[PDB]
Image 1 (cartoon, one colour):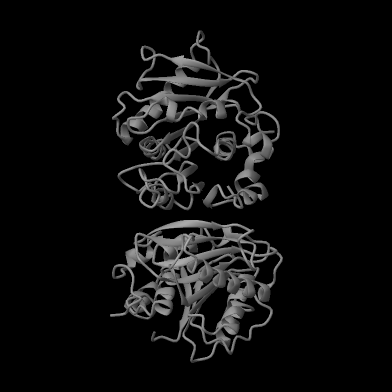
Image 2 (cartoon, each protein chain N blue to C red):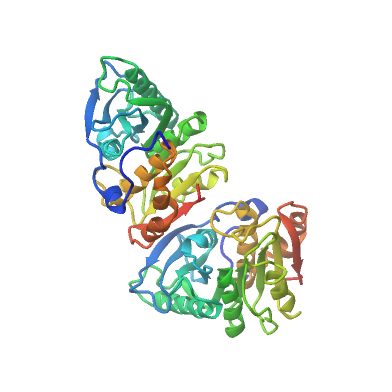
Length: 270
Length: 270
């Protein structure tokens, strides 16, 4: 038995649902408490005993938590602790966004070690992941490069000046928005994916006609995008091979006829 | 250029005040007069000429006007005609509460056509909305499903036996109470919001640690909650784009930093 396995055996319907099998609640982190980032919101499972793997999520340039926080409930309801952060400045660039992701994860560990905190004992400090939008997606790839003990990375509509992530060894799912005019896939998401070494478990999910906000809060493909983000975090943070079919097997292959997906790349099996 | 726009340009101060810029009065509807609901109280503006959009508000199971009637003064003082109703039986179920919401709106129309009545000519019969608590919030969503000519719907701490509102096309703001142990958000308000179509203008306002009564008369955050209800009815029933910033812009982003709000969802811009 895999000791990290949580929740019922997955199905397509369960993975595409707006919420997973778990109840969750949401705790605010004030600017006074927040260390190394401006402020945040923690989404954590309830009525299920952990500890759980934990994910930090960061927005893009001039953006706030509202752009990215649909990931909080979507992952929390599948047995993850999620922190969505606001950056010290909304003008922060990718390297700064990488530092703030790691600061958020470091504080989750502190909160998990604090008897008074709602998330006391909820975080497995050794099973951590990062996600982010646009320059926060650049920050996600920089965090992965600089912190290779991270278990998973999901940049979405990522933006970064440099395309060289040839040393990244963290399992990385890049979510790309076909029609993106802010972070064009041919200058950002696609070259990032192509740089990753052959030995790094990886995927590229490109959404048909996607604008730059195609994986943001309120998007019209939340069922499909959420199915991939949850499956990625289950497989790589929980080692949960019940989710492998949705990334690499017959369920995955059936997705590739959906008009919503214009392209998918991977180095399956995993 | 918008003939439905009433009153001064909005400010944070004006929107959080216990009353808006208009004076209002009340007219009791006896159980002898009331047609298709038990009885009610009408709240209507007095220092401004209409006609005005109209709203009906229904309570929850076993509950009376007193639980929901704070909305009367708050919305009437912003240029709406509001009827707070008692149901034929306090044991009426959500489909019955939906029928009674519409019967109350229909009688507001009749009174507005009744030369001797205090609200003669005050209702625009083309601009109607619904609100309700708990089973009354279930009723509100059922009314919106079955009456797509409605301009707006505001279920608050809603309860319903079914979560599927995937054909509601009426602009819907769901007000949720995070710690609700009567209509838990994980089983009611959140699934209702998540069922709404992408084409439906919508918002989800969840109050931090809120009990089931978090949006009822005498609640602890009536300035902030009433700001959202007034802004929703202005934006959608008056097509008043002056209120857009309070729902979708910088003032709204400033609210998301308040401890009182644990979650907000929307598909801005509207």
